[PDB]
Structure formats: structure tokens, C-alpha cells
């Protein structure tokens, strides 16, 4: 026989964790949460251990040990646990769009709710309660648990906007209610209620906790930017910094430790994605979610134990009618308090942020769930009761009322939110959104089929049983009237979504950028029957305010401007580039699928005109800071490269191939490089018109000794958008090398057959064919952006034309742009770098045909004419001339009239068109690979 | 001004975490560990707070709050934290190979060390210490921290065998030292030292801690097998179960809680890989490593504080010469005890487990590191001192000596291990292992180059800067004399390694199976100059003990027999199949690379003869339990399928594409299927010779109404290995469908040109061509395993030959095996399922050529003769006959003599040969992307 040995606290915490795990496991699909079961279990335990004084042995000893937990220690240990992950698991890029909508619900909402509840309880509750203590009860009861609301919101189908609003409101409500509760608790203890002291305390708490949290977050983020490869240190740093900032705010500064911890979580959500490594973030979120879960379980059991102790003390409170007949009244008042706040803020809530529909307002009511934050506050009040300011009855009554309110809310509000959402039809998947799920439910089945195919022969083990395999993926299994103008836009937006998906899979865009773009397109699908509203959801993230232009002054160094310019314009430039590239690809895909149609042209024109704002922002970036785009492109490319290397390194880790020391060294080096780059923007030099020439494909790879002495002293290559390089039909004068920018070509004799994006990227030589053959310019070039380009006189090209080893590459370089001009149907979608491989192969050879010979074009080959005339075989005598292209008849043969040079060449997700793009030997193949006809 | 408010414990823990993080960060490459810095910091803090009584404010208040930590609570909270992750992060498949070599070091080593140290201190230490106290000090000082040894072993290059031995020895030493310390502590308090009581206490502690840990592990694993998709619950269950089992052993059973927690960790390592999901197992390990780190930091600071209190109490102990002149003596004694233990166990250690070289024995000495386990034990003794049995001086001296020993070990033993491993040349990479690092360092550079290629055009942002990209991966940049018979075998083993890598990447084999196979091959490269010794590392994992055969009795149901057979014969079957497939692929690769050579043939014969044991084990599995191989194949395939689906769903979560509810539902369904599969083996039915016929590519896909009534009543299709189906040259009688098994073909007219694996897998029709044309059998068929096959009379085939739609498929089916017979060089490496796609396409020109016609074979085409005679064009008059194959001359043309049927067709990592298998347009392409000539 022992008596409350301190080891019994370990018993209590372990038993509480076991009970919480059991409650969470058993109550998964049921309406009731596991927290109410935990509270009931704690109530029963405390009742049978205090009101009956049963000999619980060591189980009761731990209960009694935890019963005298310090009010300050309870909040110091359990409140940082409850609210760190909710602040940490926050999407700042999504909270930036409804900051105002939640702030109106944060400060004014909490103030109105606290005032209404305090006035109601002071008027009604027959406990002779002072105004200070009634306002304290109202303030602590205005706190809403983020854990409960996020658990409820994911339980049933709710819109992303509404879920974000509710989660942000709950977190901000806890943040403000903590301050309100602390203020009224200080007032209730010994402090005079003079407005000067109240204002000073509010300042020292709010703007003395926010500042402390910001300072701690800045210091810890700077530290994390130097902890290269250690997940354990990174996860431990969050614990240490949060639990040290809570102490420094509560004890050393007198501020609010809870608000400091929440501010630290906000800072981590905002400014710590470059600090925590990608591998560490998932484990960090899991750990903090588990810590919040443990705090919820421990608090919901301990509060039940202490409620059972207080109300089953000397048998008055539990048996008094003034408790059970006024808990319901307090529930009614806190429900009416929510209605009052919602109704008061509605005339202005719907005009801010995401807006607020009447259905969303009805959901805003009944979504107020009280959890372990209010429970912890009331338990701290109970443990600090018994003084003259707060009697033992007052603190016990506060804790009992808060527990009853928590139980009633989690029982009724959650079940009603189930009923109301299902009644307002806001939980049904929309028609254009219950079409991409079907796509990523038939694609998953295709991936499963391919995985079965790969593991198919295995003669040593034998054949697998396909029905058994499909028994585990059975959950995966269960036109577009082009004259619509509504379904066409939906298919185009599906193509944009697929392009964003491919860009993320390729690693071209980050996860947050991909999330922003995908949510923008998701907004677009809702407003699809009017126009293409997908850039409307991206302009919040794409802004170029005019106060960046003053950075060109001497007040700051030019090299110092780049870091700020890159940091501010990083996400916006990535978003704009992804937007424009996705719409280019989707325009090409839509034309390829729908063919030539009026509605397709309408949608293409809509997309082209919508991309204007993104093009304008990118042009503003080009004109203001030339090097920011290059820096961010290099950062993006190297981030993708290092992520690919890191993934390969984890694959190597999964294989017992290399020694652990060497794998550790490689992983440490790659993570160190990744942190060194994701920490600060890469430093990239600026070319002096000689580096661009050297990097250009034409130069260095052709001229042995060109005008190199003139490179260091040459005119500015900066050309504004819309500047015409040369006119169509004019006599050749020289070539225009493209270094950086976009130039667009238009022509009349060279008809724009099917080109939608007739532009030439960097590293392209223009005007070479005209200055080689002498034929006039086939098209005019207009710059679509700030283009860096060089002009070389045609006489230099003609002089270089002396050598055949120069001639063949010159003709290939000319063909590089001829393929894009003559046949833009299938040679415009492909990139220039991919087109380099087609011409650099040995199968494509520059052959100077002799007069009277025959040119034969294969079925999977396309020929181009560089000079001379060609006459078709088997067709009417229509003499073909310079440029022009040869295509298979299924003319497979030609006639070489005069001297001619000819070159013969060789020959994306389907989300845009999912339902349309999808013997006996094949049947036997299917039987050999599946055992039946299941494909 | 306050006085030790309980909130100051939060200060202490947060400040200790911050100090530990700072010490770990600052001391990373330095010789000294961060734990000695933590101990020094704690010593300084305790000294200036007690010996000087400085006003530390709230910092000292937390120190004085933690100083009163209960001896029982300190071990209940901090000891499970220290030793759970070391037991959890333990490879059972690797410790099973050296159980004896560390059990010798576990019980006998700890006993000898404790006895020697206790006798030495009792004889020498001038504190009038009883034998019980001296033995207690020896027992607690014989504990070695797993954290310190694993940190040291990863710091410098040590062999996998030696590192595993050291880690297992440290963990087992802690496990035994806890029991020894508890026994001597109970003896020192009030218990009689009679052998009956000692035996009873040892029995109760040992086998009531191991038993309780096993029971808790079984219950928790059964629970985890039903927690489908919740990582937080899975990680919390480990905490709850460990900290509840510690209490149940220490308080409710009187056993050792530490041993119970360690046994629970062992059970989690062994029988919990299918219980914890793959997603959780990384965050779980991270969390428990962090918990161990926090426990280490807190203990190393608190022990320093308490040592500074005890020695800087009333100023005697710190200033006594008998402390500083006997701490060094105790260090010498513990070093001598380590030397004695190693020397005594060496004559029989080297005959067990992995063996023990003299260099490995020298490394075993100086590798004994004392950490937070001994520190925690001595701190518990100090906190429980002051009684009559143990005085305050005795406990203070125990704690001081243990802290000094910990400091001295972590300072000197680590440095000596650094100096000696470098001196014994055991840290240098071997020659055949400093060739796969080079392979997976040129391959990472290739992957980086390809990643730069993918993000290469991007006209909108511009071109990336390749030098900046390579500045972050610069860490990657810095014959085989075939007449060797040593380098050839090394290349073959590298090919086997590459095949295992491809099997893991494809998802064919699990991570643990891949690790076992790869470490077997790593063992092989060491003894490469003698023979192919890589199966020796797999026969520990591949065993078929004779007591499995008794399961066929009536004592147990047959349906229950399969289960135990599946878990027992799962890893061994997978390992054997991977072994055989990898050696087949490596034999083919070696023939392809080296061509025809004597040494290549020698290595191929070595591999073929060595795979005999794996073939025999698989044949034993076939004969004993026919359905186990099919069940494990189905489980493997479905596991791969579900893992691919899980990766796809993770990527889809990374994309803001699907609604959270729907994607969560998909993830939950996939994880539920994965858990339901990893919990119990898949249930697969047994065919009745009709299901196999139906699933065969020939039947159902050919006969409308075949002998189906005879399917239910037919002879047994079981054929033993080596049974000949039909003889070569005999007249055709029928066909032999292959349902399950391996059949080998040998021939002389076919000459067996270059076939290394002349076998036919399941789903193949054999003898069809002979029964169609009437020509005698081209080869004889011998079964290489238990083959399920069916025989159909040739007259049925001839009757079916009536329909042309039947005839074309029959001829294609015959060609399916003809390509493998006529041209095995290029048509045996490909699988049968892949060969189905070659014949099922429309390019198969199965045309009955007329006499006098011309057969033309393209350069990328291969012709096959089904009947008749064909004459070459432009070649000597050598008439070709039935079978035989046509190949391009660079004969491109042929002459059809009589009626003939012909068909025209169309046309792995390089680790085996890494250093050997690796213009102007191409130069321009190279310069266009990177801006220079870097490739
Ligand atoms: C809750 C969700 C998870 C949170 C994770 C992070 C938690 C960080 C903070 C750790 C909790 C610290 C609580 C210490 C309890 C103080 C008790 C006390 O004042 O007792 C005075 C008594 C009386 O002291 P005295 O009488 O000698 O003076 O002292 C103690 O018993 C001190 C024990 C301290 C250690 C208790 C376990 C702490 C585990 C930390 C990890
Ligand atoms: C390297 C180690 C790091 C890993 C640590 C993992 C710890 C997991 C288990 C933690 C349990 C710790 C309990 C300590 C309680 C000490 C009480 C005592 O001595 O005083 C009792 C005495 C006895 O009082 P009496 O008069 O009732 O008897 O006084 C008190 O009651 C003081 C109040 C203490 C109330 C308990 C508060 C403990 C809070 C700690 C965190 C809890 C969450 C755990 C989750 C993980 C976070 C660490």
C-alpha cells in the first residue's frame, strides 16, 4: 500500500493516452466526437474516486496527483500544445485573401460575444456574480477550439472558402479570447478598473506578445536556415522556441504566452517553408498534431475528473437545481450570442474577403465548437479558486459550466452542422468537379493495370491472381456537344489544370504555386458559363506596386536591391509564367482536339486576351529589374535539380548498395546545397553582350574569329515590346540573334495556316535563310517583350558561307526556323531544344540534289526545300519553289528541275478530353496477362 | 520576487532543449560530443547556483524544482525515452545473423564486467563500501549508451558487420545492466542475500519483464493491424503502450520496466512492419529519435546540476583528493574490465555470428561508451541516497563517479576509436566498392543534366544559368582486362546488384528483401577472387526445416496450414525468386556484354550451378505447399499495385486538384486495402484443371466448344522436375499447354545457338507448330520444376484448323515459341507477355506467299518461315526450308519456291559495364541549353 507516489502521474498520462486512442478508434464514423467520450470517462472516474471514495489503488493516486496541477503550469504546458499546430498548419497564401473577413470576426466578434454573454449571465445567473467575473466567464466561453472545427470540416463536404473562413475564425477567436480572459482575470483579482490601466495592460499583452513571438520566430528561422541536415534538431527547435517564448511572455514580460505561441506559429506558417526541409515538414506536422491530440485527451480527461471532484464534493453543486437549470440557459445564451455576432457582422462580412452567402452564414452559426482551450482556461480558474476574489464555488461553477458548454456544443452543433449542410445542398460535388474525380479514378485503375503488367511473368513464383488484386482496388471502379461554348471552356480549364499538374510533376513549379494555380482554376470552373475567370484568382498573388521603383535611387546599393526584388517578386513571377505557359499549352491542345471551329477560336481569343495582365506584369518585371527573372529561373531550375537528386538519394537509401557513410555524405551535400539556395537567392552575373553572343548557338559554334573586339563596345541590345526588327518582303540585310525575350512573326504570302503561338524563344537565329538564299524576308518580326538581340551584317554570313563545314550548319540553322514558319501545325508546339535533336541526327542530311534527279519522301518523313524548284511525280505540273514543304501522298516522289538543296526529317495529360480520347491475338495476350477479359 | 513556482520547470526544460540544440549544432565535426558540453554546462550552472548561491532568478528556480525529481519518476519518464528508439531502430533480419555473438556479450559479458569492476572498487576504493554497493556501482557502470555508439559509428567509416555487432552489444549490455543494477540495489536496501531469493528475484524481473513486454507488443500490434489510416494514433500508441508497460512492470508486477520497454521495442522491430504503415514509419522513427535526444539532453544537464550540488555541497567532496585521484583509477579499472571481457570472450566470439578479427577485437575495446543510461541510474541512486543503507555521501559519490566516467569515456574512447580505425585501415573504401559510388555519382550528374534539359526553354522567364546550377552539385564531379576471372565476376555481381535495384524500383521486391539481397552481394564482392559467394548470405534467410511437413496431418485443418506456411515461407520464397531472376538477367547481360568467351562461360556456369540450392528450396515449396507460391506472388503484386496507387494519391494531394473529402476517401480506401493485405495473406482458390484451361491464352480464345465436359474429370496435371514431355524428332502427337511451372528445351538441329535460359514460362503452347505443319519435334521438353500442364490430341487441333480466323491465330501462337526456338539470342531475354505485343500488332504480315513471288525483309524487320521453301536472291543456290529465320543482308530479298507462309516482325542499368558502355549541329544543341560545352 502506497500513497500518491509521483510515479503515478506516468500511470495517469499513459492510461489517458490509451483511453483517448480507444475513443478515437471506436468513435470514427459516429456523430459524437471522441473528446466527449473522454470527458464522460473523466467525469465517471472522478465521481467514483471522490464522491464515492472508492479504493482505485495506483489509478486513483495518479488522479489525485494530477488534481493539484498548478493553474499556471497547466496553461504553460498544455496551451502551447493545443494551439501551436493550428497556427503552424495554416496556409498564409489562403489567409491573405480573407484577413479582413476573419479580423472582423476576430476582434469585434470576440468583443461582441463576450459582452453579450457577460451581460446575460450577470443579469440572469443567481450567484451574486460581479460584472468582472461574469465578463470573465463570457470571455473564456467565446474561445473556439481549432481542433474540433477542423475535425468537423473534414468530416463532411464543405467548400474550401467556407472551411478556410471557419478555421481562421476559430484560431483568431482563441487568440482574442485568451487576451480577453487574461484581462478580466487580472481585473477580478486585485487590479483597479481604470481605463488607463486597462489600455496599458491590453497594449503590454497584445503588442508585447505579438512582438515577442515575432522576435522569437525571426531568430529561430535564421537558426533553421543554418541547420542543414538534421530533422531531429529542426523538430526540437520548434518545441524549445515555443515553450521558451511562452515563458518569456508569461514570466519575464507579463504579456500573453498563448498569444506569443500563436504568433510564433503564424510566423512559422508564413516565413518557414525555406527553413524547414521538405523531409522534415511532414514529420514536424505529424508530431505537432500528435502533441495537440495528447493535450486534448489529457485536458478532456483531467477537466472531467476535476468537474466530478468539484460537483461531487460535499453534495451540493451536482444536486442543486441552479446548475442543471442554468447550464441550458448558458447554452441558449451562447447560441444566441453567435447569432447576434453573425447578424451584426453580416452587412459587412459579405463585402470583404471571400464574401458570405446566406447558406454560408447559416453554417457560420452552429459552427462554434468549444474544446480544450475553454476547458483549460476554466480548469485554470478552478485550480486558482478558493481566494476572496474567486470563491471555491465560483471556480468550480466556472469549470462545470464550461465543461457542460463544451459537451453540449460538441454534441449539438456538430450534429446540426451535419444536418444543415446536407439540407442546404452545399455538400454535393458540382457537375464540373464530379468529372475530374472520375478522371483520377480511371487513371488510377490504368496505373494499377500497368503495375500488374510489369509484375506479370515471374516464372519462378508463378502468375498472380488478378481477381484478388482487383478485390483491393474495387473502390476505384463503379459527348461534350461542342456547340455549347460552356463545355468548351470547361474542357479548356481542364487542360490548364492538366498542364499545371504536369508542371508540378516535372518539378517546374513548387507545391504552393501549384496549389494557388489549381485553386484559381477551380474558381474558374464555377464561373464557366460567362467567361474564363481564372486570372481573377491570381491577381491577389500577382502585384507590382509602384513603391518598388524608388529602389533605383542611390539610397540603397544596386546589388542590395536585387535580394528584396527577388524575394518580393519570386512567387508572382512564377505564378505568371506558369499561367501563361499553361494557357499556351491549353490553347494548342484545344485546337488539336476540337480542330477548326468558331467556339474554339472564341475560347482561344478569350485566353489570349486574358493573359494580357500576366504579360504586362512580366514586362514590368523586365523593364524594372532585368536580372530578377533570370535569378528566379535559375533558382527554380536548381531547386528542381536538387529535389530530383534528393529523391534519387532516398531511393539509394532504400537500397543496401552504398556504405552508410557515403550515402550520408551525398545526402548532406545535397541538403546543404538545397538549404544554401532556398535560403538566399542565387547570385547570377549580367552579360556584357559578349556572354550572350558566346552562349548563342550560332556564334562560337560557327565563326572562328568574328567581330569579338566589337563585343565589349557595342550598342544596347534592349528592344521594347512591339519594336519591329525587319519587314516582310524587304531585301535581306542581316540576321537577328535572339538572346532573351519573345519575338512574334506574321506573314501574308506565308499564310498563318494553323499557328496560335507564332513566337521564337531565346537562342534562335532569324533572317539567316533570307541572307543565305537572297530571297526577301518571309515574315516580319515584332517583339512581344523586352528582347535582347544582336544584328550581324549579311556580308559576314556570306563570307562565312565559304566553308562547306560552315554551309551545312548554316542551312540547318535556317531550317530550324523554316520548320516553324513553313509548317507550324506540328513544329510550333515542340520546343526549339527538342527541334535541335531532329535536325542534328544523321538521318537528316543536307543533300544538294542534281537537276533531273528524283526526291522521294517517306510516309514518316517530311522534306523541306532550301533552294531551287521541284516538280511532283504523278500530279499535275504545278512547279514548286523555294521554301514550301513536302508531305507524303498517303507526293512520295518528286522531280528535281534545277539545282536544289533538300533535307528529309523523321516524323501531355488527356484531362482536356477524358471521355473521348480513350481480334484473337490480342484476346490471347489479355488472357496471358490477366487470366480473363478484364481491361 | 517568487520562489520556485512550478512553472519554472517549463523554463528548465525549454532552456535545456535550447542548450542541447546549440551544443549539437556547434559541435558536429568536432571530436567532442554535444553531451559532454551539456554535462559541463549543467556542472557550471549547479556550481554557481549552489556552491555560490547566486541569484539566478527564475532560472535557478527551475533548477531547484528539477533537483527534487523522484528517483522512481526519473527512471519512469526518462529511461523509456532513452532506450525505446534504440530497440525500435533495430534490424531483426540482421541481428538474427549474430544473435549468439552478442548474447555472449550480453549476459556473460555484463556479468564478467560487473564482477571485475565491483571486486576492483571494493578492494581499492577507500570509502568502506560494502560488497553490495561496489557490485551496484560495477553493474550500473557496465551499461553502454546505444545513442553514443550509434553516433560514433556513423561518424567514421566502419564495416556493417562491426557496426551491427557494436550496436547490438550496447543495447544488450544496457538490457542486462538494468537487471544487474536492480538486483544489487534491492540487495543493498533491505533484502537478504540468499541464493533462493536472488534466483526468484532474477526470474521474476527477467521473465516477467520480457513476458509483459511480449504481451503488450502482441496486443498493440493486433491493435495497429486495425488502425487503418491515422498516423497520429499509430505514433501515440507506441508512447501509451511503452509508458504503460513500464508502469505495469515496475508497479503492479515488480519486474524491470526498462527491460519491458526494451522487449516492446524489439517486438516492434520484429513483428511491426506490416502494422505501422509505410507513411508513418518515418515520422515515428523521427519522433522517437527526438524523444531519445531530449531525454539525453535533459539527463546530461540535470545530472551535471546534481553532481555540482553534491560535490559543491558543504565543501568536502569536490576538494577531497580521494575523488579526483580515484575517478582516474575507476576509469582505468573499467578499461581493464572491458579488455578482460573482450579477451575472455574472444576464443569463442570469433567462432560465432559474423566472427571477430583482431582488428575488430581492438575496435570492440575503446568502443564502450557510457551515456545517459548510467547517468540516469546513478542520478536515481543519488536522489534516493541519505538512508542508512545508502548514505548521502555514497549516493553523491556514485553519481559523481558515473558522471566522470561518462565524460572520460565520451572524451577518450571516441578519440581512440577515431585514431585506431584510421590506423588499422578499416575506414578506407575497398576497391570494388569505390566503383559503385562512382557509378552513383556519374548517374546523379546525368539525372541533374536531364532535369536541366526538361526545364530548358521557358521563353517567359528566360534561360537558366547552368554554372549556377552546377555550383550546387559540384560535389558530384571530381579497362576491366577480361582475361582476369576476378574482374569478370565483379562485373557479374555488379549486374546482379543492378538487377536487384531495378526490382526494388519497379516495386517487385520489398525494402527489407532488397536490403538482404544487396548485403549478400556486398558480401560477395569481398570474396570475388575465389568464386561466386553471394548465396551464402541468403541461406540464413532461406530455410525449409523438416517440421513443416507434419502440417499435412489431421491435427490441424488444411486451410489453416496454408496461413502459417505463408508467413513462414514468405521472405525466403521472395529472396529465392529474386536471386534466381537476378542471376538469369545477369547471365544474359554478361553474355551480351562480353560476347563469346571462356571466362564468361565459366562465370555463367558458376552462377547456374550455385542457383541450385535456391531452385531446390523453391521446388520443396512447390511440392509441399502448392498454393503458397501463388499466394505470395499475389500478395507481392497487390502490394506493388497499392504502393503505386498510394504514391499517385500522394502526388495528387500535393496538387490542389481534388476536394479534400474525395481525395481523403481515396487515400483511406487505399490504406485500408494495404493494411488488410499486410495483416493477413490473400485468399486464393485452387483451380480444378478447368480454370487453368480457361486462363490459358490458347483455350477460350480459340475453341468455341472444346472438351469442357472432360475438364471436371481429368487426370492430375502435376509433373515432377525432369519429366520429359516429348522427345526431339518424334512424330507430333499433340500440344502441351503450360499452366504453372518451367519447362526447358534442348536441341541439336536447332544447334542451341546462344541460349542461356532456354525455358518456357506459364501460358505457353508447346508442340503446336509440329502438330500444324506435321514436321517432327524440333526439341525435347524437360520440366525444370513441378509443372502443371495439359495435353490435347493433335487431331483436335487439326479439326479446329478448319477456320481461317482460327488458322491465323494458330500460326501466330506457333510463332510465339518459334521465335524463342529459332532465334533465342534476341527473343529469350524478352518476356512472353512482351513477345505477345510483337505478334498481336497489325504489322505481322501473315500472308500465304504464292510460288514464284518475292519475300522482302526490311533492315529493322525479321522474317519467319511457317511452311514451304524460300530461295535467297543474289546469293549462292542454298535452298532454305521450314523453320529457319530471315535476317537483313546489311538477304533483303527472297524467292518463293513453293507454297509458303511467312510472318514479318519489327526489330536495365549499365552498372555491369559502367566505364565502357558510356559535329556542329550537335555542338549547337549542346551550347543552346547550358550556354557552354559542358556535358
Ligand atoms: C502536454 C502535451 C505535450 C507537451 C510536450 C512538451 C512539454 C514541455 C514541458 C514539460 C513539462 C514539465 C512539467 C514539470 C512538472 C513540474 C512538477 C513540479 O513542480 O513538481 C515539484 C516537485 C517537488 O520538488 P521539491 O519539493 O524537490 O522542490 O518536483 C518534481 O517532482 C519535479 C519533477 C520534474 C520532472 C517531471 C517530468 C517532466 C518531463 C519533461 C519532458
Ligand atoms: C529524454 C526524456 C524526454 C521524454 C519525456 C516523455 C515523458 C512522457 C510522460 C510524462 C509524464 C510526466 C509526469 C510528471 C509529473 C510530476 C508530478 C510530481 O512529481 O509532483 C506530484 C506532486 C504530488 O502532489 P500530491 O499532494 O497530489 O501527492 O505534486 C503535484 O501534484 C504537482 C503538480 C504536478 C501535476 C502533473 C503535471 C505534469 C505535466 C507534465 C507533462 C504531461 C504531458 C506528458 C506528455 C509528454 C510531455 C513530456
Image: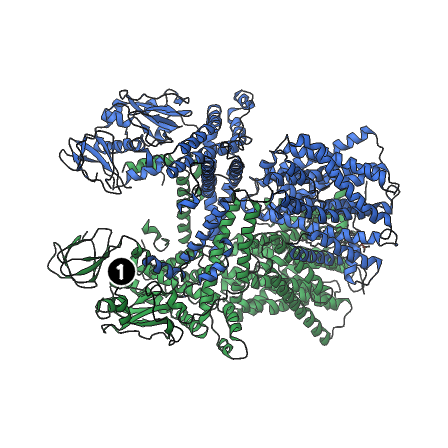
Chain colours: A blue, B green
**x%, y% of residue B887?**
21, 56
User: Within 10 Å of the Cα at label 1, are there few (<14), some (14-19), or many (20+) other Cα atoms?
Assistant: some
Res. A863 image quadrant: top left
- Chain name for mark 1: B
**x%, y% of residue B613?**
40, 71
Task: Between residue B548 and residue B797, name the one nearer to us.
Answer: B797
Residue holding disc 1: B808
Residue that lies at the very extreme toward the left in this rendered image: B877
Asked if the residue at label 1 sits under 8 Å from ligand 1, the reply is no
| Image quarter of the N terminus of chain B | top right
Please report the residue visible at 42 percent of the width from the left and 63 percent of the height from the top. Answer: B578
Badge count: 1
**x%, y% of residue B734?**
28, 72
Res. B725 image quadrant: bottom left
Res. B169 image quadrant: bottom right
Q: SS for tag 1?
A: helix
Please report the residue visible at 37 percent of the width from the left and 19 percent of the height from the top. Answer: A715
Task: Between residue A454 and residue A63, name the one nearer to us.
Answer: A454
Q: Is residue B597 visible?
A: no
Q: Is residue B161 above or below residue B789?
A: above
Q: Is residue B598 visible?
A: yes
Horizontal side of A63 relative to B535 (left or right) equals: right
| Image quarter of the C terminus of chain B | top left
Task: Between residue B468 and residue A141, name the one nearer to us.
Answer: A141
**x%, y% of residue A842?**
25, 41
Horizontal side of A786 relative to B322 (left or right) equals: left
Task: Between residue B636 and residue B522, name the one nearer to us.
Answer: B636
Q: Is residue A681 above or below residue B698?
A: above
Horizontal side of A372 relative to B775 (left or right) equals: right
Q: Is residue A571 above or below residue B880?
A: above
Amino acid at each position: 500500500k502506497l500513497e500518491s507516489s509521483p510515479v503515478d502521474a506516468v500511470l495517469f498520462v499513459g492510461m489517458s493516452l490509451v483511453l483517448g486512442i480507444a475513443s478515437r478508434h471506436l468513435l470514427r464514423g459516429t456523430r459524437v466526437p471522441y473528446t466527449v467520450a473522454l470527458l464522460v470517462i473523466g467525469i465517471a472516474l472522478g465521481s467514483l474516486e471522490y464522491g464515492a471514495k472508492h479504493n482505485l489503488g495506483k489509478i486513483g493516486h495518479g488522479i489525485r496527483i494530477w488534481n493539484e496541477i498548478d493553474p499556471e503550469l497547466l496553461l504553460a504546458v498544455f496551451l502551447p500544445a493545443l494551439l501551436f499546430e493550428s497556427s503552424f498548419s495554416m496556409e498564409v497564401h489562403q489567409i491573405k485573401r480573407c484577413l479582413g473577413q476573419m479580423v472582423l470576426l476576430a476582434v469585434p466578434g470576440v468583443l461582441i460575444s463576450t459582452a453579450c454573454l457577460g451581460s446575460l449571465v450577470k443579469v440572469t445567473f443567481p450567484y451574486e456574480w460581479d460584472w468582472k467575473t461574469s465578463l470573465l466567464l463570457g470571455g473564456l466561453l467565446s474561445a473556439t477550439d481549432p481542433v474540433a472545427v477542423v475535425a468537423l470540416l473534414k468530416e463532411l463536404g464543405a467548400s474550401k472558402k467556407l472551411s478556410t473562413i471557419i478555421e481562421g475564425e476559430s484560431l483568431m477567436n482563441d487568440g482574442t479570447a485568451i487576451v480577453v480572459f487574461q484581462l478580466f482575470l487580472k481585473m477580478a483579482m486585485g487590479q483597479n478598473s481604470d481605463w488607463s490601466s486597462i489600455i496599458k495592460f491590453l497594449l503590454k499583452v497584445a503588442l508585447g506578445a505579438v512582438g515577442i513571438g515575432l522576435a522569437f520566430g525571426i531568430a529561430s528561422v535564421i537558426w533553421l536556415k543554418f541547420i542543414f541536415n538534421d530533422t531531429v534538431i529542426e523538430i526540437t527547435l520548434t518545441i524549445a522556441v515555443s515553450y521558451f517564448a511562452y515563458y518569456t511572455a508569461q514570466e519575464w514580460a507579463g504579456a500573453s504566452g498563448v498569444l506569443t505561441v500563436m504568433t510564433l506559429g503564424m510566423f512559422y506558417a508564413a516565413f518557414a517553408r525555406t527553413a524547414f526541409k521538405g523531409d522534415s515538414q511532414k514529420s514536424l506536422h505529424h508530431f505537432w498534431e500528435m502533441v495537440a491530440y495528447i493535450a486534448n485527451t489529457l485536458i478532456f480527461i483531467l477537466s472531467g475528473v476535476v468537474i466530478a471532484e468539484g460537483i461531487l464534493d460535499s453534495d451540493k453543486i451536482a444536486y442543486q437545481g441552479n446548475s442543471w437549470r442554468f447550464l441550458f440557459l448558458l447554452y441558449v445564451y451562447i447560441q444566441l450570442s453567435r447569432v447576434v455576432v453573425v447578424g451584426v457582422l453580416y452587412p459587412l462580412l459579405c463585402r470583404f474577403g471571400y464574401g458570405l452567402d446566406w447558406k454560408e452564414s447559416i453554417i457560420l452559426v452552429w459552427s462554434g465548437l468549444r474544446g480544450a482551450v475553454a476547458l483549460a482556461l476554466s480548469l485554470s480558474v478552478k485550480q486558482s479558486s478558493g481566494n476572496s476574489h474567486i470563491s471555491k464555488e465560483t471556480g468550480t461553477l466556472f469549470l462545470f459550466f464550461t465543461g457542460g458548454i463544451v459537451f453540449l456544443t460538441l454534441i449539438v452543433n456538430g450534429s446540426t452542422t451535419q444536418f444543415v449542410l446536407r439540407l442546404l445542398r452545399m455538400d454535393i460535388l458540382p457537375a464540373p468537379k464530379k468529372r475530374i474525380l472520375e478522371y483520377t479514378k480511371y487513371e488510377m485503375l490504368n496505373k494499377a493495370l500497368r503495375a500488374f503488367q510489369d509484375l506479370g511473368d515471374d516464372e519462378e513464383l508463378g502468375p498472380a491472381d488478378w481477381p484478388t488484386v482487383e478485390s483491393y482496388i474495387s473502390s476505384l471502379k463503379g459527348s461534350l456537344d461542342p456547340k455549347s461554348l460552356k463545355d468548351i471552356r470547361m474542357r479548356f480549364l481542364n487542360g490548364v489544370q492538366a498542364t499545371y499538374w504536369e508542371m508540378l510533376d516535372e518539378g517546374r513549379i513548387s507545391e504552393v504555386t501549384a496549389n494557388i494555380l489549381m485553386q484559381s482554376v477551380d474558381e474558374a470552373l464555377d464561373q464557366v458559363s460567362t467567361t474564363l475567370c481564372d486570372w481573377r484568382g491570381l491577381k491577389p498573388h500577382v502585384n507590382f506596386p509602384n513603391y518598388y521603383n524608388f529602389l533605383h535611387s542611390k539610397v540603397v546599393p544596386r546589388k542590395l536591391v536585387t535580394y528584396f526584388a527577388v524575394e518580393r517578386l519570386e512567387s508572382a513571377c512564377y505564378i505568371s509564367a506558369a499561367f501563361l505557359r499553361a494557357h499556351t499549352i491549353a490553347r494548342q491542345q484545344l485546337y488539336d482536339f476540337l480542330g477548326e471551329s468558331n467556339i474554339g477560336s472564341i475560347v482561344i481569343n478569350e485566353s489570349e486576351k486574358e493573359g494580357e495582365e500576366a504579360k504586362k506584369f512580366l514586362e514590368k518585371v523586365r523593364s524594372s529589374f532585368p536580372q530578377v527573372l533570370r535569378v528566379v529561373k535559375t533558382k527554380q531550375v536548381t531547386y528542381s535539380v536538387l529535389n530530383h537528386l534528393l529523391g534519387y538519394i532516398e531511393n539509394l537509401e532504400k537500397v543496401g548498395l552504398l556504405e552508410e557513410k557515403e550515402i550520408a555524405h551525398l545526402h548532406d551535400a545535397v541538403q546543404t546545397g538545397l538549404k544554401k539556395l532556398l535560403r538566399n537567392p542565387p547570385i547570377v552575373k549580367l552579360p556584357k553582350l559578349s556572354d550572350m553572343i558566346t552562349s548563342h548557338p550560332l556564334s562560337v559554334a560557327l565563326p572562328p574569329a568574328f567581330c569579338e573586339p566589337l563585343k565589349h563596345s557595342k550598342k544596347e541590345p534592349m528592344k521594347l515590346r512591339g519594336v519591329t526588327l525587319y519587314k516582310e518582303g524587304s531585301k535581306p540585310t542581316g540576321v537577328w540573334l535572339i538572346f532573351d525575350g519573345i519575338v512574334k512573326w506574321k506573314s501574308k504570302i506565308l499564310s498563318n495556316n494553323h499557328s496560335l503561338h507564332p513566337t521564337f524563344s531565346h537562342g534562335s537565329t532569324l533572317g539567316l535563310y533570307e541572307v543565305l538564299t537572297g530571297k526577301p524576308y518571309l515574315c516580319d518580326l515584332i517583339t512581344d517583350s523586352m528582347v535582347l538581340c544582336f544584328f550581324i551584317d549579311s556580308e559576314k554570313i556570306l563570307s562565312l558561307q565559304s566553308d562547306s563545314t560552315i554551309d551545312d550548319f548554316l542551312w540547318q540553322e535556317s531550317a530550324l526556323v523554316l520548320l516553324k514558319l513553313l509548317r507550324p501545325q506540328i513544329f510550333e508546339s515542340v520546343a526549339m531544344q527538342e527541334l535541335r535533336a531532329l535536325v542534328s541526327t544523321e538521318s537528316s542530311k543536307l543533300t544538294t540534289y542534281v537537276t533531273g534527279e528524283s526526291i522521294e519522301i517517306d510516309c514518316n518523313s517530311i522534306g523541306l526545300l532550301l533552294e531551287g524548284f521541284v516538280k511532283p511525280v504523278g500530279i499535275k505540273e504545278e512547279l514548286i519553289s523555294s521554301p514550301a514543304a513536302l508531305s507524303p501522298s498517303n507526293a512520295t516522289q518528286y522531280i528535281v528541275e534545277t539545282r536544289a538543296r533538300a533535307i528529309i526529317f523523321n516524323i501531355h495529360r488527356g484531362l482536356m478530353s477524358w471521355p473521348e480520347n480513350i481480334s484473337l491475338s490480342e484476346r490471347a495476350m489479355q488472357l496471358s496477362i490477366f487470366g480473363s477479359m478484364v481491361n
